[PDB]
Image 1: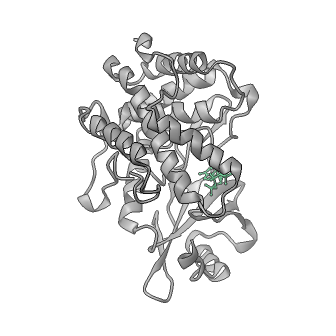
Image 2: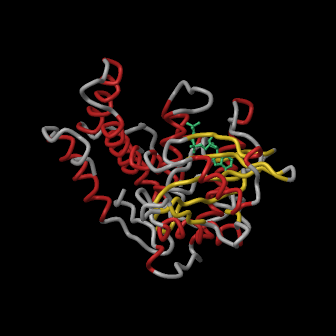
Length: 329
Ligand SMILES: Nc1ncnc2c1ncn2[C@@H]1O[C@H](COP(=O)(O)OP(=O)(O)OP(=O)(O)O)[C@@H](O)[C@H]1O
């Protein structure tokens, strides 16, 4: 982001990171610069990830909410990429930028193992995901926010009039209609809570059967089942091995997943009926995301094809898959 780029002096800030985490520049290796500057850190045969944002993008209060939730999960025995306390004991280190803002550094453990590959993509993985997500939801039920200042967002706070062309009347009607239905869903301790909100196979590592999640940047309050539907949406979108039949792959994924999940959390079967609304809601979000990403002026025929496919799905309230999830009772 250009306002942040304008301020960042990588060598100056990374020297701070050296003073703050005890890892020399030699051992700090650039990885990405999208929503954070991301570096891998290596020391004593161990690996860590360092992320850096800024106050122009995120408040420390906000990120402290994430840190608090990770601590709770780790404390309860869930394998997560734990934040690493700086030499001053902090999970977030604020580095003054010299002009009234701060860079926000944080370091996490590098999750053991690798992103899943074709040999790992099978019913045992989908079962394991189910077990792991069930443990996660179970543990979030006992999470106690320490103060309202660190409070994360509600399900409907990250719809598309800001980013979509204002003449797409039918898009907004369907989306409005969808969000109004969803607002009426019951929220209680056994249906709704702080959840990861962005589970896919880019966001976890697999190490001889053991899952560890990372990228908790966007955690928020949401329904347990929507947390689950977001995983489903992503695995339907970019599976590691392509599937032949969408509905039957959706059905089997959720069968394997729910068998594992039922070992670890009790979520009422009435929730199954709302998997297709939640898949549709994620479709709406993506469509809004692609309008923010795309410059409609400089966009080719393929980008417009993508946009068109999404647009007619939304407009016609088309199911993302035809599988009937109520049969997995
Ligand atoms: N705690 C962590 N443990 C292990 N790997 C991590 C951790 N955090 C981030 N990564 C990995 O380091 C990089 C983080 O980069 P970033 O989140 O900016 O990119 P991404 O959008 O996830 O993926 P890509 O850049 O490949 O499209 C990714 O390759 C990510 O999978």
